[PDB]
Image 1 (tube, rainbow over the protein chains, first blue to last red):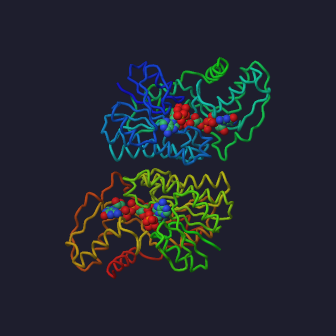
Image 2: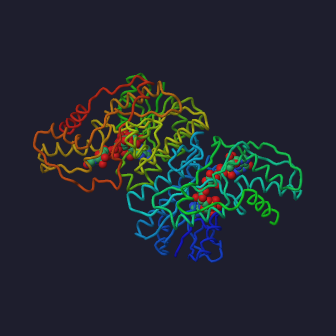
Length: 309
Length: 309
Ligand SMILES: Nc1ncnc2c1ncn2[C@@H]1O[C@H](COP(=O)(O)OP(=O)(O)OC[C@H]2O[C@@H](O)[C@H](O)[C@@H]2O)[C@@H](O)[C@H]1OP(=O)(O)O
Ligand SMILES: Nc1ncnc2c1ncn2[C@@H]1O[C@H](COP(=O)(O)OP(=O)(O)OC[C@H]2O[C@@H](O)[C@H](O)[C@@H]2O)[C@@H](O)[C@H]1OP(=O)(O)O
Ligand SMILES: Nc1nc2c(ncn2[C@@H]2O[C@H](COP(=O)(O)OP(=O)(O)O[C@H]3O[C@H](CO)[C@@H](O)[C@H](O)[C@@H]3O)[C@@H](O)[C@H]2O)c(=O)[nH]1
Ligand SMILES: Nc1nc2c(ncn2[C@@H]2O[C@H](COP(=O)(O)OP(=O)(O)O[C@H]3O[C@H](CO)[C@@H](O)[C@H](O)[C@@H]3O)[C@@H](O)[C@H]2O)c(=O)[nH]1
């Protein structure tokens, strides 16, 4: 009946809160933005790095569910901020887990991991299933791999109720800049608004990612909390690989001016996973989840968001 | 040739320093205690958690080799100090790597990892080789798995010269208390000296570990520095599994007096790897290394160290 979402003012957070409120769940959300407000959410000021405040907030609210979304979410920025990505993602998670363990709460925690935990996938391994070797290629990936490992250990050592996800690329209106669909859509609309030369600036167009709309993601998170098996890991993904080139092409075909493409070398990463496509069989079998929103719709709605801003 | 050993005043460090000085390597060593001192080592005061002081030391010395041993080495203690084990092992390592990166030094770094990175190994996987998946069971294991992943990433992203070890249990005279062969030997000699009732307090006797004498370990580290392949991971182990029961029985057979055995529940860990036995084939093939000192001899010399004060 009672859910706590850390990082509720983030991209996924707002959609998740909306989704839970519609399932008649009482929603509490935490953020560092002491002015942030969300419809039907009790908002709580919390820095996930303040271990004693994490333990106070969780002790006060006594949630039945925690969806732990507070994190440094950028792969790109983890190269520059390796330690900060690790302190926030690993230690923030530990503070949450230790709060529950200490309060001895009857609570299920969903920890949010990443397809970056897999990293380099052997061609024979794709689409990747949950038993696949973890070979992270980015510092972010190392942080999420550590979160997952600790999740499993807390289940084993302390009898806790934790489910870890490995979420693949998630997209939709409201995602911050620094992520590919936002970075591209934003330039396109600026070009339409004659605020930028008709030339779009891009990074690596050869990468392949598995994209799912944030609205489908939060349904999967809800369903996992309800039907998932304690201590299991679940891929949350569409099972379809799209080249970044084709994400760009889909977006450009929706623009109402002709647009040239140009390499921006500051968008390249020191090392990157060339391809990530996941198997969602475990998730589908456990929950009856299916993605519903096609990539084309997601991308169009992102363009619409910038256009109406 | 100049070598820098971090954590030089630790168990492995003192032996490694002695070994390197015998190879006509100029040895510089770091420790947090300013009242240390080692034959033929230039001692430097350094806390590995001080990123700017780490850079300064590495900038000053301009070493050809760094043997990075500074760490929180206890698996037992990692359950109580999860964040400290993480900050020291992962961030300490990042400080070293970034210092070398910044100074653009022509330097090979040996990062020291652990069989705890493997964790739970399937019977068909034993003895484990370096491509086995990582399924750590202890927070310590997560910290070392992260060190290894990051070492591989710095090679790939930045073109650095780094070799990572996965070292299995290492033993010998001078190891601190809190590790099994020391905890057992100390009590036996205290019992011989009539300082303790003839009952030894012990933890889990059913665990299996792969033991190698520290004098052999440091030869492996030296040889890897010379002959190892950049970006490769090497198990450093004997390939022989010994039950802790049998470790104890070997020690009791060497004692003066009949000694009974009793469980001390405080020696039990929340969750533990039942069995770790490694393949040393990659190391032997690359370097010609072989373990020379039998387990019985290591255990004997440990007892002698307590008996001789
Ligand atoms: N020290 C912290 N204490 C409390 N919250 C923190 C702290 N550091 C960061 N966050 C928050 O986490 C939220 C993460 O949201 P987004 O960056 O928009 O990511 P998204 O909602 O797409 O991803 C949610 C989860 O899904 C994963 O992909 C990602 O790593 C994360 O675990 C942000 O609002 C971010 O908030 P802020 O914008 O830094 O104030
Ligand atoms: N923040 C720190 N800054 C500088 N040094 C540090 C810091 N934290 C710990 N150390 C040192 O690392 C040394 C590690 O030595 P032992 O605990 O005796 O471990 P051992 O020498 O058996 O193992 C060497 C390597 O092999 C692995 O077993 C272990 O994780 C480590 O990576 C200790 O002298 C330990 O010294 P101290 O007793 O904690 O002062
Ligand atoms: N951001 C960005 N990415 C670009 C650009 N050009 C090409 N790309 C490429 O587009 C791909 C997706 O990058 P991002 O959208 O930044 O996300 P990510 O690095 O894959 O990480 C996202 O997905 C993970 C799940 O796999 C999430 O765990 C993570 O938090 C994030 O949402 C990457 O291969 C990136 O190099 C650009 O201009 N901007
Ligand atoms: N310390 C200790 N261990 C005991 C005792 N009784 C049983 N044990 C068991 O003896 C085994 C060895 O434990 P330790 O000597 O504490 O070492 P460890 O946890 O295996 O870790 C050591 O080896 C790793 C390499 O695999 C190293 O990475 C790590 O730094 C450390 O040296 C474990 O299964 C432990 O539970 C006891 O009284 N004391």
